[PDB]
Amino acid sequence: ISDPVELLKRAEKKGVPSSGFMKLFSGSDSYKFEEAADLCVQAATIYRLRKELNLAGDSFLKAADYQKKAGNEDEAGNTYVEAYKCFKSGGNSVNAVDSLENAIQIFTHRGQFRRGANFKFELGEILENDLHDYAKAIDCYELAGEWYAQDQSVALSNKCFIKCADLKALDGQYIEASDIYSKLIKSSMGNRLSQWSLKDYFLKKGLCQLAATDAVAAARTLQEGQSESNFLKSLIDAVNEGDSEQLSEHCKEFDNFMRLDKWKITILNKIKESIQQQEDD
């Protein structure tokens, strides 16, 4: 059979719990659901080949669910990833989000945390970069980095917490972030292979601190940076002297020996303001 439509048509007539003489005559049910699964997958594939993606993703969803009615949890989630891949590649972020959410539900309940995390991250990423639900992207970037910890795979766990920290700084949870940064610093010196990146944590931690108008903590955290950090100093001052011009300048300068990335620019404007408001206060 080569018509996805037909394949799917049969896929339905078959993936149904049998009863009566049928149940008796015909071998087990799961054998049927698998048979149904295998049908949708065959359709999903023809669709994928044809570049109809949303139809391939929608096809896989069916297959996946058939697969779990057959009790092949792994084969299922694996399939959910396939559906996600399509819905993603097809720009259907909403459905691509669903798809993953199942794979994860499974990978998680099935105890496969390392693989869970892997997708928990992607999920967060789409949640963050596309749908723009930062409040939920943060939740994943956290629960994902958390699993990586147990798996003792530090490296990755950090990649999460930064995506996590950076992003809370925007939503304005200034200290929680400077905290996550603190932790990202402590559990990053035990690895002399991270040394280089450790500057940004400090600076970023200080910037958060200043943004919360806590210039002491910043001054402190700058000192601790003795066991970039030079630009933080010039800011801990421009602030301590309500001069939204020395600051507004040091940033202008620092933008030469290191163009500022969106984050810093956001956070830095939130600081320049906290100064002006204090001048007109």
Image (cartoon, helix red, strand yellow):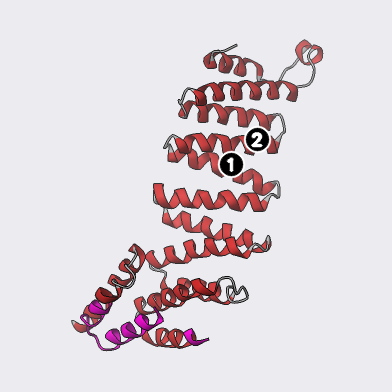
Q: Is residue 265 above or below residue 211?
A: above
Q: Is residue 121 found left or right of 77 in the rendered image?
A: left
Quadrant for the N terminus, please.
top right
Q: Is residue 1 above or below residue 109?
A: above
Q: Residues within 10 Å of mark 1 (few under 14, many from 20)?
A: some
Check disc 2 and report the residue beneath it: 76
Give the image location of residue 75, x and y in percent: 68, 35
Residue visible at 37% across and 83% down in the picture = 230
Check disc 1 and report the residue beneath it: 102
Magenta region, residue range: 225-250
Q: Is residue 219 found left or right of 3 in the rendered image?
A: left
Q: Examine the image and state in which quarter residue 233 appears.
A: bottom left
Give the image location of residue 70, x and y in percent: 71, 29
Element at label 1: helix
57 vs 102, nearest the viewer: 57
Q: Do labels 1 and 2 touch, CB within 8 Å?
A: yes
